[PDB]
Length: 43
Length: 258
Image 1 (tube, one colour):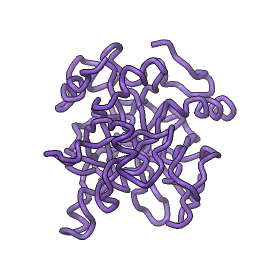
Image 2 (tube, rainbow over the protein chains, first blue to last red; image 1 turned 90 degrees about the vertical axis):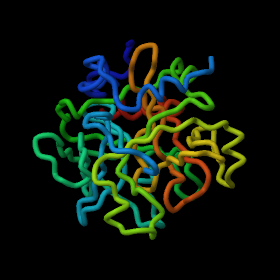
Image 3 (cartoon, chains in turn red, blue; image 1 turned 60 degrees about the horizontal axis):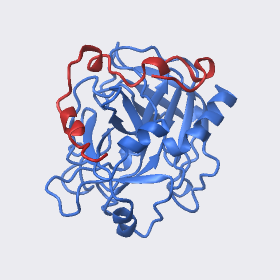
């Protein structure tokens, strides 16, 4: 994950963004996420 | 949120409630990008003909909440707003174009199991993830149905609400309304002819349309709920503000004022 904004002005948070403490942080998934995954048929 | 479901505690830690101080009513959704900058519909802040000229002093923001009103102790943290930056080409007189708002907290929000930022799109992600028919998750404390069926009190979910939605072909949507779907918006909704119904409602305006990347496993706020089709608007598809298309402006502000 190659960051953008300046840690200094943006604020702490970018590096580990978008990964869920209770979810991604344990491999564990959420009741409906496989729904999202499977919507990706294009490319 | 219509035909949404309850959210598992934590399922979207980025979710922020945008509160009115006096009186106290829910005002809008709002994503969190970093322990100090937060994202919302500009219209959630400055729409005059619905009486909105809100300022930093009038509002709070509520981070990592579940129960729409149980002041969840030892979980939700209440940040105060230091300043609100509104895309300045956003002109509430024309249309919903550039319906975007950045809010700087006074105090860096602590992260917990329930507070934790959302990633943002890079052109790379946009192009692989923002496709006609790809589904994306919208979360909110907007009302649950058409507003004079049953009783306000039912229809106002008691915890945070979740709903995924397919992205809509730009002609399909464009054709569907006399509002200009600009360069800087996208459309989410199930097929006109469809067997679920999911959408966002006024109260949901401001929060995050979000998709998870399968390449790097991360959650990216492609949009802002800009004008859902759920509830009273009952038009055809929801418009979202394209977050990426405005990343240039986002940085202009942070860097200037962070």
